[PDB]
Amino acid sequence: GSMKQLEDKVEELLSKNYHLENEVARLKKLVGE
Amino acid sequence: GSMKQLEDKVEELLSKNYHLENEVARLKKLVGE
C-alpha cells in the first residue's frame, strides 16, 4: 500500500540513478585521463 | 499529503536522472566520436 509502491518507484529511479551516475564516472574517466 | 511528497521525491530523482543521463550522453559523445 502507498508507501511501499511509491517508495518502490523512488528506489527504482534510485537504481538507474546508480547506473547513470556510475556510467558518468566511467565515461568521465576516459574524458578525464 | 503522501502522494505529493512521495511523488515529489520520485520526480526529484527523475530530475537528477535527467542530469545524469544527459551528462552520460555528452560524455559518450566524446567517448563516441
Image: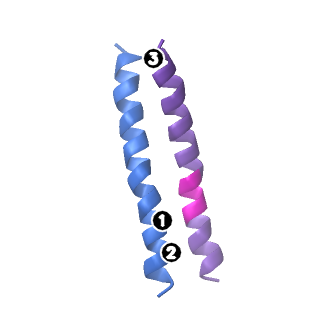
Chain colours: A purple, B blue
Instruction: Using residue A33 as the reference point, say whether residue B22 is left or right of it.
Output: left
Residue A6 quadrant: bottom right
Q: Magenta residues?
A: A10-14
Asked if marks 1 and 2 touch (Cβ < 8 Å), the reply is yes
Mark 1 Cα-neighbour bin, 10 Å: few <14, some 14–19, many ≥20: many
Residue at 38 percent across and 48 percent down: it is: B18
Indicate the chain on which mark 1 is placed: B
- Tell me the residue that label 3 is attached to: A32
- Tell me the residue that label 2 is attached to: B6
Residue A32 quadrant: top left
Helix, strand or loop at label 3? It is: loop
Task: Name the mark on residue B10.
Answer: 1
Helix, strand or loop at label 2? It is: helix
Callout 1 and callout 3 share a chain:
no
User: Where does residue A22 sit, x and y in percent of width and height?
Assistant: 56, 35
User: Where does residue A27 sit, x and y in percent of width and height?
Assistant: 48, 23
Q: Main secondary structure of the magenta part?
A: helix
CA distance separating discs 1 and 3: 31 Å
User: Does the magenta segment cover residue A13?
Assistant: yes
